[PDB]
Length: 45
Length: 46
Image 1 (cartoon, helix red, strand yellow):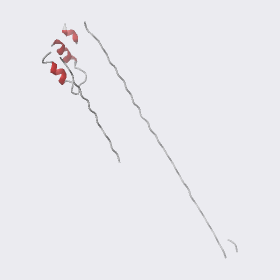
Image 2 (cartoon, each protein chain N blue to C red):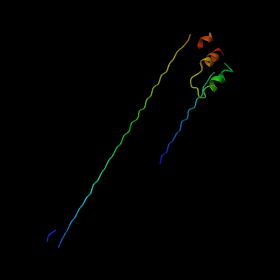
Image 3 (cartoon, helix red, strand yellow):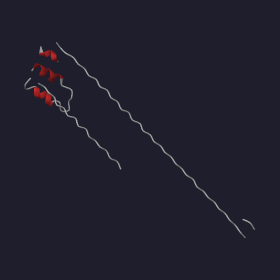
Image 4 (cartoon, each protein chain N blue to C red):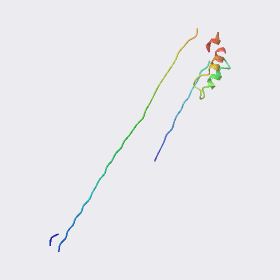
């Protein structure tokens, strides 16, 4: 302002950015086998 | 929006060749994968 004349200018600006990525997992595998022989029929148990 | 797909198919075909006891081991495969010890002994005796 100079002296009548008056001037005023105000500017405001804000920005915000956010990113969140999360991944959690588990996989399990297990195999077991057997084999046997027996050299009366009652013993088959 | 949420969508879920469930699909599980398990089929068994036991072969027990005990004339009458042969069908027991085949029928026992429904929900019971492991063979019964007593039923196995009965089939062995047969």
